[PDB]
Length: 246
Length: 246
Ligand code: NA
Ligand code: NA
Ligand code: NA
Image (cartoon, rainbow over all chains, first blue to last red; front, top):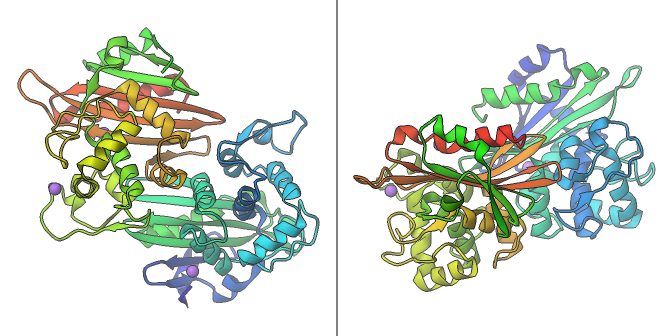
């Protein structure tokens, strides 16, 4: 937000796992960000499942999602993951990253409204070409790690162009770790393993509330093998542990 | 509360530890609750720290608490626990049960407004007499485990006499365990070790959201020694683990 500085000593955690990626960590009270790689922090990637955050907000703003108690019913027709073949709440759909639930939300939102909200949210390159139910997974939408933390800061502050109520609803849906000393809100994403010399992207984005401080973060990495997927949490977790945050 | 049913199969969790207490567990709604002790389920006890839940809602409704980013500044004067001697957010004050923060909230709310809201909330015997900053600590206010689950169900459903925004703010402050499969919101309470032939009371109340289901719970127990305090979480946790909820 206010400043950004490269800290190449965080590269130790990437090097140990042979990962090409970036971590951006911003401290709210000092309005200052740090990253291991300023260049990659500005590079723009498919959001994949991280797009569930804006999509949920927009679904609520448009009334497509009634409220946090709506149940997305399973129609019994097979889905790509057994964990998706069941009725889901909004939190449940976000937590398991149920693609087909959010494809249907996008379809009902429609292109004109989706375009309007991504403009209000300043979300990425705001390019929703590629089909209304796939632009964030295989279409032309791209967002950087810096843009992710800017968006998440706005959500945390209830400053997005949506009701505070709907921003609070989506925040509750994103809580992933609760301790007496700190609270973590987060979302993963994974575009797939990509092509030969054209790897996919994996993301972990979110924020940590600790004492009266708030830390916004966004991680992404190249990925060509699902077996590396847990590194999208363990590398950023080790960095935030070394920083004394969690 | 529709009907309360006795369930004898939990008694082993109490007798193992020589605890006199009650657990109330309600699936979906307060229409159907189960308990180990029908009489004690409706017996009224001092709420202690569980009162921070209504106190926070009333603080927000009255504007005494400005919003969920309010910081409760520590004036540097001694407080009864070192963990209270610091600036605290609302979630922070709740999670460490910072009595003095909630005493000052209660003082600013004042007796007239406090009485009005406990009546709206149907909060126990609604007796706030004896001192506006200690009626839930050593005064005459009493609430049962059944009334706790009814109040918490209203809060879960956003049906208390308060804005939905303020209900959502307090719910976020009460998250205590987050797992992909389930989310726990809860609050502890402890009146003290009592006096001769007159034990104190310890509480754990909350709800669990799992798949598309919700479970409301309230536990209390007699206690005359602080060494027994962890049982207020371990007995109900073991019951809910055996029920398959957590
Ligand atoms: Na920022
Ligand atoms: Na004190
Ligand atoms: Na305890």
